[PDB]
Image 1 (cartoon, rainbow over the protein chains, first blue to last red):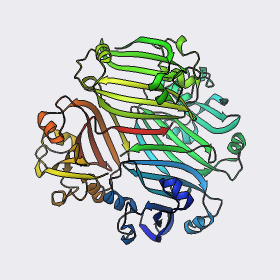
Image 2 (image 1 turned 90 degrees about the horizontal axis):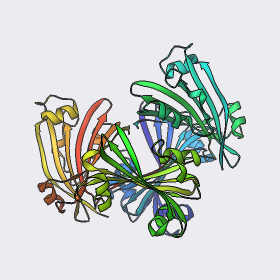
Image 3 (image 1 turned 30 degrees about the vertical axis):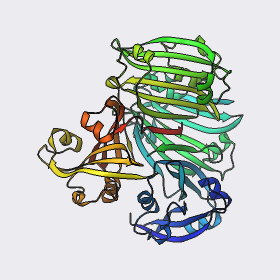
Image 4 (image 1 turned 60 degrees about the vertical axis):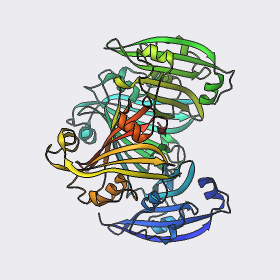
Length: 142
Length: 141
Length: 141
Length: 142
């Protein structure tokens, strides 16, 4: 386990119709968008495709996300009070498959995450993992 | 309308994989149930489950169209700890047929094992078509 | 020894609070059970439960000293999603009386709601004298 | 939504009986101890009384926890893999009522937590919240 990453995208853009729904925003408002690929022993194991309300985290594009995760950084900037996850088994988009070095037919674990600071949505990410390279594991008392 | 069909309910030798899961020898008896769940006549889950026969000796007496195997086991032994592993997989050919899905349909696999104190009691492989189920959670920090 | 006593088991109108809890009209009918659970003669929990009466038409016919409301409801509808809210509260005068606590003793409230698909099935308030109950668990991160 | 905090205690001390059992150590071994009052919009919401294995986080005492929470810091120092919780409703002690700015008869939510990194206990905390000011919420598919 030699963990390595590459920040593929880090930019401002309009929320548009999808981040408007995801972050309770108007389509015209600005978001910041980072896309990071994570590698284990040089093999892609996760895409983290993250959008952040730009007013909440004005300095987000100034960060080096090879040195702190976008989540860790956000947690210092705003008090994150609530989170949501949705886990699905999907086929990934063409360009996501290319980034992950998988064939298009390879099932992937998707975890969609949203995080709130008080009642306000802060960030929405899609974590996409090749299904042959990552599993969620845990143990819990009853 | 939720409905289910009990496809298998029988006693079987544990074999290698179940013996390992439940710390048993391979010739030791397990009970095995395979149940398909339906929403509005559409398959949404296969539950393929095994239990140590010594722990729930009346398991084969139950009508699992009336109550789930898990809720049944809850009542025969105190279930105190569970482990799970979630993966995105393609299902086996026979699973695709029971679930009425495309061979290429991505599926959520949930493998579970549940314990009564330090004894593993039951283990299950739960397979859901990707288009038909998701796990959702929302929680304060 | 665990014992319990079913204190209320009746049909009533949802009214304004169950209208909000269960997304129902105020005049829609619900079933209401209130059960007190004891440990060695000493009250440890009130389960005050409301159920959509169309979902579980036979709820009033059950003997809940023999099976819990939640276990019964599990058999009548697929219960697919649950919500839990844990608060530290002071209990209402009548609840303090049932629990044999002073009005100022803090209580652990767990407020639960369970759905079957998109449909809210039941909402319950579990109230525990803070001195007699704790919630405990452990889980991997 | 704004989180601020006041560090009341930051010191090395003997584990004692409690922390010896919580953190699997000798009662005479040194542990680090922080007591911080957390505010949400200037109103007290939590007293976090936290103890930390000095061997795992040797530089704990050196931190400015007005800039970061102890948990965030600790999760940087070591991978936190497992958490244990005990939740109770209690009345706070008189000094705790003064710190939280609450009525003596206010029901408080008490959470006692331990966190492991692998099989080593890293930290144990006693968190007391005014019951009117915090609760635990979750919704989850079954």
